[PDB]
Image (tube, coloured by chain):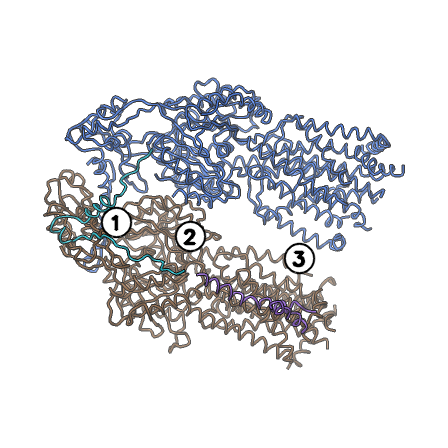
Chain colours: A brown, B purple, C blue, D cyan
């Protein structure tokens, strides 16, 4: 068609192709770089942060009202909640196709208008993804203390970082917030007649400036100011109610952050705003940090990161770049060895880079992320093929527009069939879409480009001696034995195919390691701190670890329900090509796992930061797999989950197994005797005020200093509420106005209660976490799911043991995969419309992928499935071309077409060869495509020039 | 003030003027296109 | 043109058409079912609810400033509002194109008393009405079951925005005070309530350490039961003053729920999940002998609709194929030309699948089928007869009149996208489906078809009358011109509506009762009403909703009832009674129940009627004015007048009369000489008398209000109220009648402000006769009165619907005739254009035949008829003008005489596909019959003038 | 044209409260702030409707 007139446009079409190439490079410049795509779905939590309350008083008075007022939000997919020590934390995750802000809108519509008792204000969590935690840092200083570092953190660092666009919030952990503590000795409390609430409603009063509007004098108008604001502690100590200690202080600690031999420090977590681009924002937070370290912060106090996303970005750019480079190099080298001429070799070679720019421009102008993971897996050696044939004709023909217009039609056909097979990759949604779709996009675009280049530029550009007739011999080398080999090898693909693993993700190595560390129930912050310290001791022993950071307890935001018995541990590593040791990766994890089993009271779960996030937001807990144990009674569900825990611990596939919910902790329960207080003139309110303020210590008011704010709190003095006897000694004020110890009107005892209550859509359950390491998902879940639901004592209150994790993930993924995969068959059957045999030339590559997979002990995950998609896409072109050129007709084409076939089968299965190399972050996903494609191509090619021509002489003649 | 937009506009013109002065270069295709393209300064006078 | 490559592309076009077949089946398998399209307009209402408060301290300062700010919301179209005892509810309806969540957002922004937003549902969102039945369980138990089991469950069904309770008994904790022991005790209701409220809290003491352990401290002071409350009068369980009462078959006091379909979600789809939920409730959750049983279930209507449309399309199909078989003679050709219908349908689903167009059963039932194949059967006729080797030599002869004829029927079917609102929502998927399928018929007839390779006496009878056309100029044009006005003065006498009855599964009632009536008396009246409604063999269930519910999306009193009347399948109607006759038997019967005024409507349409006009009736008359007495006077006039017109069936004043209220004003100077605050008094009335809830006791996942109020017979009458006491500043009791005027004063029950105008509504139904002539007569009789002015009067309801529809008709008509003449240019065109009245004749004589009117449905029917009619005219005139271009008069029997069969064939299939659609027997045929009638009737009297007056016209003009 | 946008510091009659005095006199600074905000300033107390 246009191959005729494009020839006389040589210069012109070249010129525009330069200009296009310019816009190509430009298009690559304004292209968002993703080293790790936003795997997470659209979620949103609602946080009710009550200060000082216990679980039973939090679930019934908040989680029940919220869940009552939420369950019907337009967009829901999964709904979970956890009620804990003064926290109602309701996680909602929406269906695939719901916009973030839309969802947050509907949710926020449903959460407001409520009524929460203890002044509880249900807000929403910041708009961020699990993988949003992009910049973890800590404030170091040899000389300054933790209180000062905390002040710096709160009033300078976090504010400054918040100024970075794309940063939704900065999460603080550790340090010490400063209260204005007021220590009341209860002896002189019910001695001066008035009690706590009288004070806390009086000291709450005298701290509110007055404005007097305008007072006129002559022609001037002076505004009137009344300065009645509590400033320093001396402005505080001199307050009267009728005619105690006063010190700086801190509230009881939510958490303690530790590090390399540093028990108590402070960290910030930079939360990336959803959808915004990591590196782009990273530039900003970098500039901000430098501005802080060099200008804002006092010298001698430095912000030092320990986890930065741009590190992984660098590792990824390096590795992927290395892959593409080695790829193009190898393709050009084999081009040289197979053509001989460097001129023509380069001519076909430039089809690759030029097409990239033609693919970039299409991705750029129509909103497609430059996903590095789905780019390093590009083949190159598939792109040039069109151009290659346009060469193979011309070079082996010695006008040229006639041979190019000759081979053009069998290339547009080959274009579609190879650009078609990639289309099913657009089917699957969820987390397997954000990872593989840009690859198929880029391939289709670079195929439009490859075609345009081959047919509208390539023409315009103006040991084998033993390999040749050896092939001419085997051609001559029986229809029964032939179809025998065909069917037998086919059942080879059927057997070897039916016997293979079925994961979902090939791990995907990040720079570091994340730990879900679990301590004994109801321990103190101090003890938890000791334990965490010893854990970091145990971890730093290994030379492979760079920094080790512990988070015991919870951050001051409330986005985590964690008790002091819970630790999260960040474990950073040295560069993989730097380890003076022999340990692998899973060997390092296994070693640390062995060492961590040697410490008492410490159970340790292994994962990675971003993936811990998304696994959590998916399942409801931080592990690969989970087993839910629904039920309305706690004891029962705990028993069942105990059985399931031992049962799962049994199987040689689950590397970690443990119940997610802490056991019932102890608690001093102060009940109030009604009839006694009645018989004595005492109000329940008074008791509650004594507990909340005198024991608990509620903040009275708030004091301002410059741009800063602190909480004035009043609470009974030290050594007064140490234990149940002492508390019982505390007194109130009856109608007689004197003294009544609460021990007279209140039953103060030692009871136990639940630590966390994981409500699941108003169907209470108990999570049984399990991480697997070694065995795949099918071999594992076979035995596991087999044993479990057939060893559990039914039934009573619910108790239906369900599953979660990458289970239904893999299930739905494979489901849609095998939904769209057979659909593309008829599509690439009407194209071939004779088509039966070419269609039957597909399972040839299958066994080729299976042998290489079995070789490398891999599994049939989504990645390798895509590998079989590329494989099935390209391996049919060879059949098409060995059919178009093609009972003695075999040697009319076979011996002729044998050379470019190998040439195409060499370049394709050589671009993915460097992408078959491990090591370095960013290859984990691309590798299983290489393992399938290359190994598939080698056998499938080694067979397509043998059994297929021996199948073409067995048509319409038998 | 208005100098933010002054700089924005003027620099923008300093950006997207070779955008067409190269586009017209290629478009005009009867060497000689340079001659035809020199009609610009004469008008600018 | 493209028949050339296609003839050599037989196998390929066949395979790809098989592909479009598969993707078409798949496309239909992924298409939303809509049996009753969301007729509603984009609306949302704000609820400012003040519990226990009367009807003037709710409008003076609440509805007014809210109306001020809200009036300025973007995209606003109509703004109404109603103020009364309990609440101020403001309705806002928006312009078209205004997206829901967006609008609700603007509204929500502007309203920022505690004004809230009503659930996001259409007035036809109430898809599953049910009642908790039991034989052994008591209404309180059923109430708690409802509240804490059933509703919380159904609220989980995705697509269910909310569930509305009505009936049963909410349970509260209450002490029954006797002020006798409040006399010399100097504790007020306020100190009592502040005391009894402030001591309900469970403090936490945070973390108290003990060695290596850190135990949380729990203080518990939350009240648990009336035992913990008891530490005077009788402290017991109880219930607040009853909202409304719901009644059923002999059952006066039960409890029901209303499942509200979330806006813009597929009814049947959500009904699936609701069915799952309900099933789960009966099977596993609820106690035994407690069953949730529905009485309205949208699924039923979807069933009857797919049965009716299914039967219709099937009958039309088999009839059209019967025609093809009888005509061609060869079953082979009949089949190969029939398979255009399923092909196009599959080829139209895909285009509706990707444009996301729904599958309106109401409008897909009105597809002609025999109008689709006319693009194909003319070719087959021209091959299997005219030709009697090279197929596409014959397909070229009738090609141009077919491409242009079908693009003409497409350009004619086109301007249905003109009108908006309800008349669009109803008849829009048809326009698209027909368009796509038409283009598919084009793409089939001149592609896949070329690849495929008693009449005796009818023949020369035609030759005879054609020989009668030899001359008789003034007689032919005589017939033409005479019948022109002959139909111009037949559609001038036709009645005009807006749409036919549109039969749903049931019947809805707006039953009005005497003013001020107690809830007991109301309940009895409803009991009787329902017992008289069951006096028919055709009523499955009868449900009354007297009074108000839980939410507050209705400002109703016990004098107001809404009744649901469910029927038996029409199939099983032993009593020989038409549905309309059942309605009039019901109306007559109801005109024998004392005090019971009954409005007649339907459960889905009543809602949209209300959201549109104002009140729940087809027609309203709004009497505006800032004076209550006078507007009510004029309204009395308009009521008495309108109720005399033979067309108006029910007529009432929507706003209920003013009612007595025992009113307690406070004497300022008296309490200024006794040292008493008005707040002490108001506390006495709100807490003591009113019985305001004091606190909130929790039990499991449930919660209840703790209320303090005086015992019964302590607030019995105005004397008793005035006689109870309240302390003063001197530390001694003071009787209430000593400082407060306790009297009996008449106040307004309901204040309705629309577009910032106080108005009263005379609601009325058009049932009985017509709309055009009726509204003409009545509205003319209205101008007699209207005693100005001090007051404006307007009409509303389906009057506006008629206006918009008519105006849109007048807009559309010349728009198409422009392009139609334009397409008919070149390939003089006025001759062909004037084929429309030929079809108009039958389209209007058939309306008078069965007894119908001229609705938007039948209008669209004419839009359809014009296509096929002008197609026949085009074919005739084209084959004529090409055959020839007296020796020219010979062509009138040559080029026209041989077009007998194609024209008759087309005019038959296109007129037999709609015969089954002209059937009524079933739900879902109540909108198709207009188009069916118009086309069927207007095509059997159009062909007879296409084959007679038309050739004579051509011969007369071209000389 | 040229001018400093912000108006210069204006005079104010500032009523600071001596803590130790109102302490040794038994008085709350809240009382003073109410004296100013209401007595001097003049805050609206309620809302009348006509
Ligand atoms: Zn986390």
Residue C755 is left or right of residue A868, and the answer is left
Q: Provide the chain ID for the residue under circle 3.
A: A
Is residue C224 found left or right of C804 in the rendered image? left
Query: Residues at badges 1 and 3 in contact (C-beta under 8 Å)?
Result: no
Residue under label 1: A218
Tell me which residue sits at (31%, 22%) in the image: C744
Is residue A48 visible to us here?
yes
Q: Residue furthest right?
A: C886
Q: Marks 2 and 3, Cα distance to the nearest angstrom?
A: 42 Å
Residue C137 visible: no
Location of residue C920 by image quarter = top right
Mark nearest the camera among 1 and 3 is 1
Q: Mark 3 points at which residue?
A: A830
- Residue under label 2: A93
Classify the position of ligand 1 by quadrant: top left, top right, bottom left or bottom right: bottom left
Say which label, 2 or 3, has the lower sequence index: 2
Chain on which label 1 sits: A
Up the image or down, C194 lies above or below A523; here it is: above
User: Counting residues from the N terminus, which is met first, the one under dot 2 or under dot 1?
Assistant: 2
Q: Distance between the residues labelled 1 and 3?
A: 97 Å
């Amino acid at each position: 068609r246009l191959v005729t007139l494009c020839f006389n446009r040589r210069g012109i079409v070249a010129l525009v192709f330069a200009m296009v190439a310019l816009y190509g490079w430009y298009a690559w410049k304004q292209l968002p770089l993703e080293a790790y795509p936003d795997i997470a779905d659209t979620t949103s939590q609602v946080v009710t942060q009550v200060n000082g309350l216990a679980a039973e008083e939090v679930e019934q008075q908040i989680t029940i009202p919220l869940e009552r007022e939420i369950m019907g939000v337009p967009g829901m997919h999964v709904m979970r909640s956890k009620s804990t020590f003064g926290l109602s934390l309701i996680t909602v995750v929406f269906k695939d196709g719901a916009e973030d802000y839309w969802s947050r809108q509907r949710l926020q519509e449903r959460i407001n208008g409520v009524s929460l008792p203890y002044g509880a204000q249900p807000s929403l969590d910041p708009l961020t993804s699990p993988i949003g935690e992009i910049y973890r840092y800590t404030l170091v200083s040899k000389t300054r203390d933790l209180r000062e570092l905390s002040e710096l953190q709160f009033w300078k660092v976090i504010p400054r970082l918040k100024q970075v666009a794309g940063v939704v919030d900065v999460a603080n952990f550790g340090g010490l917030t400063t209260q204005f503590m007021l220590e009341f000795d209860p002896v002189m409390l019910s001695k001066y007649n008035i009690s706590l609430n009288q004070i806390t409603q009086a000291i709450s009063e005298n701290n509110a400036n007055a404005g007097g509007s305008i007072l006129n004098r002559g022609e001037q108008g002076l505004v009137v100011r009344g300065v009645g604001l509590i400033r320093n502690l001396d402005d505080l100590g001199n307050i009267v109610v009728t005619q105690g200690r006063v010190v700086l202080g801190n509230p009881q600690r939510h958490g303690i952050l530790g590090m390399d031999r540093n028990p108590d420090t402070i960290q910030g977590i930079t939360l990336l705003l959803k959808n915004e681009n990591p590196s782009v924002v990273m530039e900003g937070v970098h500039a901000a940090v430098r501005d802080l370290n060099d200008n804002i912060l006092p010298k001698d106090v430095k912000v030092v990161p320990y986890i930065d996303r741009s590190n992984l970005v660098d590792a990824t750019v390096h590795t992927v770049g290395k892959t593409l480079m080695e790829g193009m190099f190898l393709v050009s080298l084999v081009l040289l060895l197979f053509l001989g001429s460097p001129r023509a070799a380069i001519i076909v070679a430039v089809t690759i880079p030029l097409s990239l720019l033609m693919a970039f421009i299409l991705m750029h102008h129509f909103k497609i992320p430059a996903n590095l993971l789905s780019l390093g897996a590009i083949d190159f050696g598939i792109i040039v093929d069109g151009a290659i044939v346009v060469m193979e004709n011309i070079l082996r023909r010695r006008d040229i527009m006639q041979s190019v217009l000759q081979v053009a039609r069998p290339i547009f056909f080959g274009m579609i069939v190879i650009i078609t097979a990639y289309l099913p990759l657009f089917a699957f949604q969820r987390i397997e879409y954000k990872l593989f779709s840009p690859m198929a996009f880029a391939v289709g675009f670079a195929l439009f480009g490859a075609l345009l280049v081959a047919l509208l530029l390539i023409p315009g550009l103006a040991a084998l001696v033993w390999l040749a007739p050896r092939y001419e011999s085997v051609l001559n080398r029986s229809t029964r034995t032939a179809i025998g080999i065909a069917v037998a090898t086919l059942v080879g693909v059927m057997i070897l195919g039916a016997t293979i693993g079925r994961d979902f993700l090939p791990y995907l190595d990040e720079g570091s390691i994340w730990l879900q560390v679990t301590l004994p129930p109801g321990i103190s912050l101090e003890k938890a701190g000791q334990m965490a310290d010893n854990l970091r001791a145990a971890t730093m022993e290994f030379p492979e670890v760079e920094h080790v950071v512990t988070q015991v307890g919870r951050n001051d935001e409330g986005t985590d329900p964690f008790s002091p018995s819970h630790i999260e541990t960040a474990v950073t590593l040295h560069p993989y090509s730097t380890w003076t040791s022999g340990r692998d990766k899973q060997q390092l994890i296994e070693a640390m796992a062995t060492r961590f089993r040697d410490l008492p009271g410490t159970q340790v779960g292994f994962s990675q930061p971003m993936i811990d996030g998304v696994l959590d937001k998916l399942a409801g807990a931080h592990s690969d797999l989970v087993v839910k144990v629904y039920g309305n009674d706690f004891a029962e569900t705990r028993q069942v989950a105990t059985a399931i825990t031992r049962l799962l611990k049994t199987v040689p596939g689950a590397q970690d197994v443990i119940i997610d919910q802490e056991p019932p902790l102890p608690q001093v329960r102060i009940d109030v005797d009604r009839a006694a207080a009645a018989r004595l003139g005492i109000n329940v309110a008074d008791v509650m005020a004594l507990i909340q303020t005198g024991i608990g210590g509620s903040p009275v008011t708030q004091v301002f200093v410059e741009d800063r704010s602190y909480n004035v709190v009043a609470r009974f003095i030290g050594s007064s509420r140490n234990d149940p006897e002492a508390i019982g000694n505390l007194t109130l004020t009856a109608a007689n106005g004197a003294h009544v110890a609460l021990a007279q009107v209140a039953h103060i005892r030692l009871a136990e209660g639940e630590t966390t209550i994981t409500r699941e859509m108003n169907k209470r359950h108990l999570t049984v976490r399990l991480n697997l390491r070694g065995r795949d998902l099918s071999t594992f879940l076979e035995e596991a799911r087999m044993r479990i639901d057939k060893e559990v004592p039914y039934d009573r209150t619910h108790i239906q043991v369900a599953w979660g994790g990458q289970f239904e993930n893999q299930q739905r993924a494979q489901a849609r995969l095998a939904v769209i995969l057979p659909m593309v068959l008829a599509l690439m059957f009407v194209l071939l419309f004779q088509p039966a045999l070419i269609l039957m030339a597909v399972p040839l590559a299958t066994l080729g992928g299976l042998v290489a997979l079995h070789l490398r002990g891999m599994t049939l995950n989504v990645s390798s499935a895509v590998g079989f998609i590329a494989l099935f896409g390209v391996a049919v072109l060879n059949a098409i071309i060995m059919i178009a050129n093609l009972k003695e007709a075999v040697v009319r084409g076979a011996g002729e077409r044998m050379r470019p076939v190998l040439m195409t089968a060499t370049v394709a299965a050589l671009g993915l060869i460097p992408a078959a190399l491990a090591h370095g972050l960013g290859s984990d996903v691309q590798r299983p495509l290489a393992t399938v494609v290359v190994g598939g191509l080698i056998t499938a090619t080694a067979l397509t020039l043998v059994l297929l021509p021996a199948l073409y002489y067995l048509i319409e003649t038998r | 003030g208005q100098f933010e937009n002054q700089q924005r506009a003027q620099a923008r013109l300093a950006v997207i003027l070779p955008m067409v002065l190269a586009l017209m270069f290629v478009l005009l295709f009867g060497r000689q296109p340079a001659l035809i393209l020199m009609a610009v300064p004469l008008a600018t006078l």
